[PDB]
Image: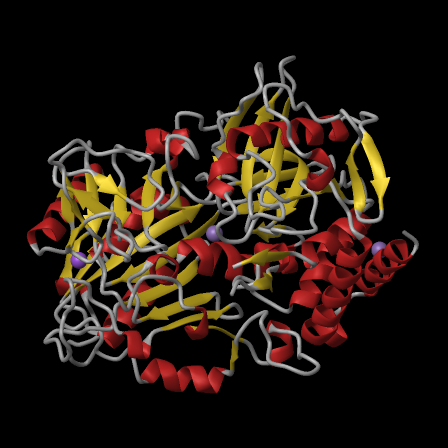
Length: 612
Ligand SMILES: [Mn+2]
Ligand SMILES: [Mn+2]
Ligand code: NA
């Protein structure tokens, strides 16, 4: 300095710039210089920091306390800022093809590329001066157990206390992360709500955001995530999707591991034998429900490692070892009930931040598909801060409304959920919502067929069925064809014990629109079958799509008369159509980057169907 504008020491309200590692200081100070915050708060992760921040947010009307529960809070957002916006989510690389495959006829659905020069322009129109009159919070956070060889540290700078509070729950954050980090590498995460003081635009519902300029950007070659304009979930808690899926799946490709949109659960049978399973489902398909399921089969136990992301790597012995990189659950609120997910009900009544759900007059929470009558007198305020009755046509909670809750509070949290070595995965499950044609469960014929099954995933979102390969469609950090190649290469890794791959459909319907399968806790019966198959049991029958359970192989005792023939029906005409549209989709969307072995699997499936 020959003046006094570069050293931001005088503005530090917690911590010290001097005590930070060199590269962390440069990241903080360089962005302070750019964003011009009034204050810099280096988060310590302490309980005192957290409670004081919440009370301050309560002071400014940004959140309100839910008096019915133990330390629970409600945030109601600006209606314009209620979800991840895929259309404003981008990945910057030198070459487009490294990010997305170049489609044959249409526009790509597998990602969104932005040139570095387009990004630099975008960035310049947004970030300079954007934290003016605000505190820049510095969040050191670990994705994964501190000291896990599979864990990765990031630093998030944000002008949102809502993000700070939500990040303390969803990641491991604070001073211990900075001590652990040392001079090591970290992912750089910069976020601003995009509303510098003095405000130029109306503040709606005490929720700062800038919908017109919203942009969620990833720069894997710079190890940067840069996010502007939204304070909501996937756009602002940068550890979760931006880091744990997009950035991380690229690192994974580089380093020979996997970053996947998968729940992890442990399942123990009546003889004390335990297996870990990963599953990738798209939206409205019940990941959290399965990860925390209350099994109906006596003697069986299900325990939760994670409900959204898995980082997985083969060890020296060939075991596929997985960690949950998250520290909490960011679950969809509506449809969560004692019936659908009793273990989540148990988790969320303490130390939980709720967003965009309804509030009852006694200070409780309410949402569509909650299966709880309210006492006479008890009234509801909707997520829009309006008086509400179940006689209205509008939902009382936004469909994408959330709970944000500590993982440690899950009554069935797995005792190895934070083990640094990770848990050994023995099965991988894919699934979606398919009202027709797709059996309750089938098993892939080989690794390559299993990778194909993942690639071909489709789910009901008039109703529309869309592709969501590996449940990773909004999350690929790089070219999807190369992603398939990466999966396929695992078969050629020496010593690798390749997990069995299954596909499930909890959602098949008859001719009248009625679900053919009871689901929920009863899905433990499907899991029992998978457990036996992993153990080599002779419980399968070969079909053109894979192995299905033999007659009588599935434990249906205590269920009524389940229509097994319709549940497991495989029609030639349905599957002819299925294979044709998968072929057209993969050709168009993956094109020149479709690996040979996926083309082969597709040909093979076509051939098997043609013979029935
Ligand atoms: Mn998810
Ligand atoms: Mn091969
Ligand atoms: Na609000």
